[PDB]
Amino acid sequence: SSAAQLLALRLKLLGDELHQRTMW
Amino acid sequence: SAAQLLALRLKLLGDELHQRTMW
Amino acid sequence: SQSNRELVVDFLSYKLSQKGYSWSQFSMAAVKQALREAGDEFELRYRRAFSDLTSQLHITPGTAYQSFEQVVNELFRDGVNWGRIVAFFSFGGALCVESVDKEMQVLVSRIAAWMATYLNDHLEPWIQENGGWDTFVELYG
Amino acid sequence: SQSNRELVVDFLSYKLSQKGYSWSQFSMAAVKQALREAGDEFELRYRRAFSDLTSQLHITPGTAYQSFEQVVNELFRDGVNWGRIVAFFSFGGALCVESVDKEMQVLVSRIAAWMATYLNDHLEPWIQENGGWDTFVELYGN
Ligand SMILES: [Mg+2]
Ligand SMILES: [Mg+2]
Image (cartoon, rainbow over all chains, first blue to last red; front, side, top):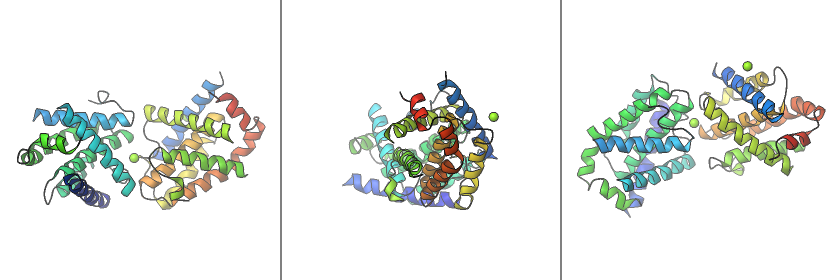
């Protein structure tokens, strides 16, 4: 619930970081 | 309730490791 | 659709094998290998940065889905990209490992269906409009 | 005395390293290596037989020791043996790994203190009456 909200958030940032890192 | 089962399973595998090693 | 379900089962059997579990006890190769290494690095990056993925998630056989749907819907709320898909696969594997760690082995087949359904109905569109899984391999591996 | 804290700190350092954690981020040889291999063999059997030792325990900083004391008291309620001591180390080790997993790394030094205290007051007696730690390496030496 409150942890899934934080977990969802953290999955975004790390996922978007992996994207931008691989993209370059 | 889950801790009482964890404690329990720790005993059985602890006594099994004890009896197995002692032979 | 069939390759999507075959992709999900492979990644789940891989993550389950890392914790000593077997897939059959419960229920293109470049794409498997690339997604495997990406999921390993991501989960390792997540544990270092923040925490375990699903340990704080107080999941139960009744709370599994409607917490899974809350995470994936938020993860892809504002778009889809390759890194968010690696995040999607890693979250499912950690959920499947967590289900076995809590003696809920009936949930892994349910999670595999929930992932494969989201893969086809909501994720594959972005795949075909972005080079397909072939683009994912030339970028990871 | 200090050799027990030396053994407790060593085991927790080993179990924290198996998931990528470093001991300093939060805070003899034959007996250490013997407990490490026996503690490794114990966790593999427990995961194979039943489940994860701590992932099903809903641990919070307010119920940390409250859960630690009820497990070690039940484990050593009706006696003490070497395998039960191995179960004692593996449990506390798995507790620290869950503490860092659940973002409660302030509990690592606390669990380390709770274990070394119980080892001295309630297990060290039994250690000496059964030949000391030299018997543990005699039995678990290969
Ligand atoms: Mg019993
Ligand atoms: Mg866990």
